[PDB]
Structure formats: C-alpha cells, structure tokens
Amino acid sequence: GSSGSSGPQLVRTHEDVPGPVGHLSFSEILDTSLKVSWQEPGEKNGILTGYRISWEEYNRTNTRVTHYLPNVTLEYRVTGLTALTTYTIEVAAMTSKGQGQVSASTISSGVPPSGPSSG
C-alpha cells in the first residue's frame, strides 16, 4: 500500500518542495548502463508532479545529465557511463511548486561483459 520506514533524521525547517525520495536503488547494472529506482518521499508536501533524476560520475559533474519523469515513475535506466567506474545518481522529486531534496547515492558500474561469455 503506502507505508513509511523509520523517522526522518535530516534538516527539515520551513520548506515547501518535497524531501528525499524513498531510497535510491540500482539494479541490472552493467559497465555503462544501470537501472535506477526509488520510492515516494514522505514529505510529498503536496501532489508530486514528477521526479528529477541526474546521474554523474563520482566527482565529475561534466558528466551529469538532467532528466525528468512523471509522478508515476520512480525508476529509470541510465546509459553512457563507464565500466568499473564510480558514479552518483541523484533522484529528486518535483511538485506543483518545484523540486525538493535529492537522493544521491554512489554506485560503481558493474563490469563490462565484453562479448558473450568471453569470446
């Protein structure tokens, strides 16, 4: 249904936009392609209008992208990364006011298969 998980332990103060999405999730990772998943934030603070995702190397914004998703999607496949490389995927939420906090989780590309089996 719609449950939470533990209490929010982060600066809240006065804020309209939403907070950090559920939790970053990475699957079907490869050498230059990985899937990103998350959940709905408990600080919806309104009716989510969408989610702003942004993937980028460990410390290389130059390799950052800006994508947009609806308030129905919470996962997206990333592509154009690097094999055996550290990356950071930031997933933010967008409301009728704007974008709020962002969940950035460090993830290092899986590994390049370089052909089937080995070849």
Image (cartoon, helix red, strand yellow):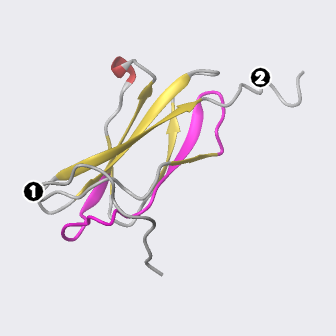
Q: Residue at x 77, y 27 (%)?
A: 113
Q: Quadrant of residue 97?
A: bottom left
Indicate the secondary structure of the residue bearing disc 2. loop
Instruction: Of the two numbered discs 2 and 1 on the same chain, state the one appearing first in sequence.
Output: 1
Residue 81 visible to the viewer: no
Q: Which residues are magenta?
A: 28-51
Q: Is residue 95 left or right of residue 8?
A: left
* Residue 89, placed above or below residue 18: above
Q: Residue at x 43, y 64 (%)?
A: 6
Q: Is residue 34 left or right of residue 102?
A: right
User: In this orientation, which residue lies closer to the viewer: 57 or 81?
Assistant: 57
Q: Is residue 64 left or right of residue 45?
A: right
| Tag 2 residue | 114
Q: Main secondary structure of the magenta part?
A: loop
| Tag 1 residue | 14
Q: Residue at x 40, y 19 (%)?
A: 59
Q: Amino acid at mark 1?
A: His
Q: Position of residue 69 (x, y in %)?
A: 34, 54
Crowdedness near tag 2: few (<14), some (14–19) or many (≥20) residues, C-alpha within 10 Å:
few
* Residue 23, placed above or below residue 89: below
Residue 53 visible to the viewer: yes
* Residue 63, placed above or below residue 116: above
* Residue 43 drawn in magenta: yes
* Residue 2 drawn in magenta: no
Q: Amino acid at mark 2?
A: Ser
| Quarter the C terminus occupies | top right
Label 2 to label 1: alpha-carbon separation:
50 Å
